[PDB]
Amino acid sequence: ATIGRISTGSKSLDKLLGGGIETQAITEVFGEFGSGKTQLAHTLAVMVQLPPEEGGLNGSVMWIDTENTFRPERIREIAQNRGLDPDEVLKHIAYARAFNSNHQMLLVQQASAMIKELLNTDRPVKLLIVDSLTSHFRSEYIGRGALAERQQKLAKHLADLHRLANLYDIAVFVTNQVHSATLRVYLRKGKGGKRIARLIDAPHLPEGEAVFSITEKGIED
């Protein structure tokens, strides 16, 4: 299948991403708390649901939360301000809270069965969010030989993530605070409620930067 692109809500940021975030890839967005990673995840969970003419893929979402940062109220606000039905937007976001790194790995594996069933529907899964990919791995692996073990589990988790994205034509979006993903985006605060995105690593895309805002519509220019 050909690559689908999900608009982030920002024209500037979509331009940097060659149209938007891609299916059949793991897009990693990293930054300090408040850099806009979570607002971008919330905006994408709504945007993917829009028709292609609006920047979406008529798709369903699966969201894995390691730190309880998912906000239904924010999804609802973004949905309403984009002229979508908040109830329908929420019902197309399959949500799961991971309490440890092993639970997190298991949820990715269990998600394959769910995705299979939605493939021939009008709204198949086009987006899988993992916020925030490493929080459990960093807190659990402390002591002698902890670092080498963490790297091994992360690599397998990311391989399980890559497998779903290619096999089912899904865009995998992961967040991180501060490893090989297909696209790395460094996020930081600009001047005001403005953020700056820096494309660090990309195989088909040139390096660069884009500026965006955080509003009642989630993410825009």
Image (spheres, rainbow, N blue to C red):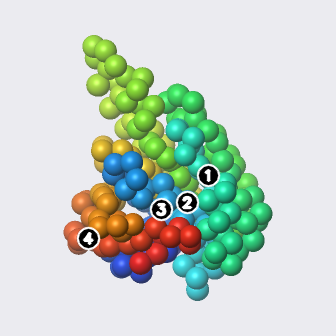
- Mark identifier at residue 3: none
Q: Earlier in the sequence, mark 1 or mark 4?
A: 1
Is residue 205 left or right of 106 when viewed as pictured?
Answer: left
Q: Earlier in the sequence, mark 1 or mark 2?
A: 2
User: Most extreme residue toward the left, as rendered?
Assistant: 207
Q: Mark 3 points at which residue?
A: 40
Rendered residue at 45%/31% (across/down) = 136
Disc 3 to disc 2, how far (Cα)? Answer: 5 Å
Q: Mark 4 points at which residue?
A: 209
Circle 4 residues within 10 Å: few <14, some 14–19, many ≥20: some
Q: What element carries label 4?
A: strand
Disc 3 to disc 1, how far (Cα)? Answer: 12 Å
Whether the residues at callouts 3 and 1 have beta carbons within 8 Å, the answer is no
Q: Which amino acid does label 3 sit on?
A: Leu
Quick one: 173 or 187, which is closer to the camera?
187
Whether the residues at callouts 3 and 2 have beta carbons within 8 Å, the answer is yes
Residue 74 at x, y = what percent? 62, 59
Whether the residues at callouts 4 and 3 have beta carbons within 8 Å, the answer is no
Above or below residue 204? Residue 39 is above
Disc 4 to disc 3, how far (Cα)? Answer: 16 Å
- Mark identifier at residue 71: 1
Rendered residue at 31%/60% (across/down) = 189
User: Most extreme residue toward the front, as rendered?
Assistant: 192
Circle 1 residues within 10 Å: few <14, some 14–19, many ≥20: few
**Residue 204 makes an appearance in the image:** no
Q: Earlier in the sequence, mark 4 or mark 3?
A: 3
Q: Name the residue under label 2.
A: 42
Circle 2 residues within 10 Å: few <14, some 14–19, many ≥20: many
Residue 100 at x, y = what percent? 53, 28
Whether the residues at callouts 1 and 2 have beta carbons within 8 Å, the answer is yes
Q: Is mark 2 on a helix, strand or loop?
A: helix
Above or below residue 142? Residue 152 is below
